[PDB]
Image (cartoon, coloured by chain):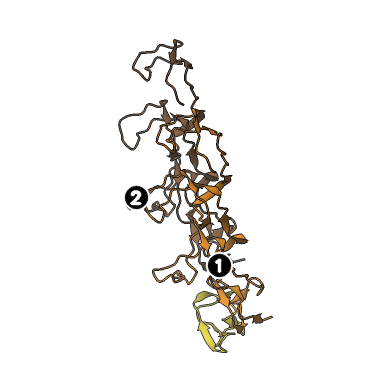
Chain colours: A brown, B orange, C yellow
Amino acid sequence: EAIIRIPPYHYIHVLDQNSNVSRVEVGPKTYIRQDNERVLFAPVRMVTVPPRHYCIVANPVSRDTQSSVLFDITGQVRLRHADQEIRLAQDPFPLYPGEVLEKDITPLQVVLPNTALHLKALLDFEDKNGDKVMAGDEWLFEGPGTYIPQKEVEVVEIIQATVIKQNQALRLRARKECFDREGKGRVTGEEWLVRSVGA
Amino acid sequence: EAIIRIPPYHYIHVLDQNSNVSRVEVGPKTYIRQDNERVLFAPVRMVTVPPRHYCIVANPVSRDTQSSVLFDITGQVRLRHADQEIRLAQDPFPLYPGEVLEKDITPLQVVLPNTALHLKALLDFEDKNGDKVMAGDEWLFEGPGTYIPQKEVEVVEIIQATVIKQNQALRLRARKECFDREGKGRVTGEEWLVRSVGA
Amino acid sequence: EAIIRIPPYHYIHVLDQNSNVSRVEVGPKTYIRQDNERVLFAPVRMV
């Protein structure tokens, strides 16, 4: 059917069968298609993101200074084929051609007061404070709070703080050459003891 | 049938099959539909809220300064796709398009004099007094009274105050680093004793 | 069919089934009709 039935917060993709340009048409409009706006898929929901949630979209659209979705000379959208994008709470964002939802809608990542996250960088990048990060650095997201799940970082594990009662101690074994809480250099495998009470 | 039979406190949804605009038509009126006001569902009751009750409506309508239901340029209602809304006692409110009743009609939440509610914030928000709240803070709704059930907070559990008779005491174990009633810093797992008589 | 195929020097009549208004639509345009622009007759020559 040449008439297409797009609800107010839905969109579809149309291919220009004369110039290969795929472009997303969003409602609200009762749209008409010739065979230069050939429909690809259905007006299906195109679900949005609830507040304090996040999504990973693969091959995102390049955005200008004003965060404007860029297009090519032919009119095709400007993608980031070698990147992803983390979408936080926002409008029912349009899925431009090539933009495939890498990881679907999901709740956020909140950490308990007495736990931590093993945040390991997968690829080289610079943090918001901007000092330096290797390709494979590991740091510890601390206690009560919430992390912003990024594409350059990965949560290796959740680490529950071990309760140390009085008249007890913890035997720590370093996996790599490093320092400790007090400032004593620890070589790999050198087991030491911490007597601090608490968690 | 082109004639539609809307009782005084009922409403339905009509789609404009020319511009995709879905809009709610409320009685009282014997309404007439062309194929630009195509009916979606029945004039079924559209139940209201009794006093001192609450409902959760998903994807609520955006409201202006005068709490006016906003519409888009095309005429479609302005929703909050990434939010909910708590509706207290009021008129048989109209369910605008997209507005789906997340949680149906229910009684309120009243607390016994010797019990409390474990109110944990699920998402970051600011309370009415407006000081600060984390994404995962926990506080205790106190005894005799009634809480206003919000979307940003969750009742983890109901906690009945434990009766402490004279010549008796309670062994309290802190789950996290914190303070106590008297002002003594308690580390995780450090069991202490409270000898106050009462509940 | 909701899509109507009007040659450059042809025209048809459309009735607004909501207000009875009949009005002539002339090409050239590949016109679209809802049931407020109901076509009456063909795009025939109109000599």
Q: Which mark is residue A160?
A: none
- Figure quadrant of residue A194: top left
Q: Is residue B63 left or right of residue B18?
A: left
Q: Which amino acid type corresponds to the residue marked 1 in the rendered image?
A: Pro
At horizontal 46% and vertical 56% (from top left) the residue drawn is: A91
Labels 2 and 1 touching (C-beta < 8 A): no
Q: Is B134 in front, or is A9?
A: B134
At horizontal 56% and vertical 49% (from top left) the residue drawn is: B114
A64 over A161 or under it: above or below: below
The outermost residue toward the front is B167
User: Residue A96: horizontal and vertical position, in percent?
Assistant: 48, 52
Mark 1 falls within which chain? B
Element assignment for label 2: loop
User: Residue B154: horizontal and vertical position, in percent?
Assistant: 53, 49
Residue at image mark 2: A64
The outermost residue toward the right is B1
In which quadrant of the rendered image does the N terminus of chain A lie? bottom right
